[PDB]
Length: 184
Ligand SMILES: Nc1ncnc2c1ncn2[C@@H]1O[C@H](COP(=O)(O)OP(=O)(O)OC[C@H]2O[C@@H](O)[C@H](O)[C@@H]2O)[C@@H](O)[C@H]1O
Image (cartoon, rainbow, N blue to C red; front, side):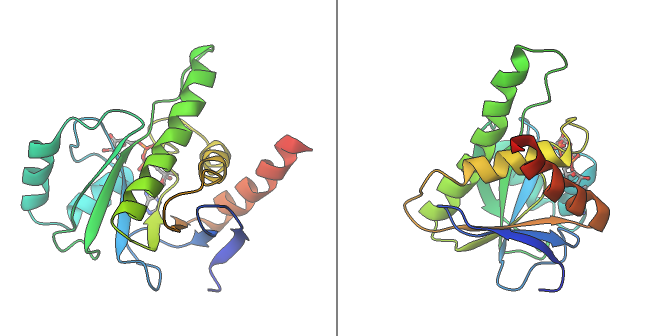
């Protein structure tokens, strides 16, 4: 646990900020989150890395399940990507000029809430998760972390610990300063 920048206490469960590749499972995380699109298609970034390491049956399962509405999440088997299951969660694209912005912050928080409720229903205690929406969907790491730390305030039926993984130390340490700074 030397990769942990900070650990936050939240109703859902502890949220750990971890310097590591999403494809390098944290100890005890058998379930990973895909930062997915509504069509559940392979993309770049985290989605690319998960599909890159999986069988064709994953695309087949997604064909059966698509679309996953923005703000929602849906599970599939992992198909050899290194995890037993994948939670495909769909972040909104960041609205470029409000008021859609405040609407989109709620939808980003909802995506994280949807991950937690899903994991709780499957009795998955730990989940490895990227910073939803912080890649091509335009959010910053701090915006995505702030959303995760808000979403986890909603108490779930069973505790779920989010291990948030990003391979760049500076991105996470920076985000860990900006989150409290907003409230300062
Ligand atoms: N291997 C990786 N491991 C951990 N974090 C990663 C990795 N690759 C990217 N990240 C980071 O995770 C966050 C999410 O970035 P994206 O992967 O681009 O996901 P998102 O912004 O939500 O956009 C989703 C869209 O992009 C496609 O990958 C996906 O199919 C969908 O269309 C960003 O912080 C990104 O830098």
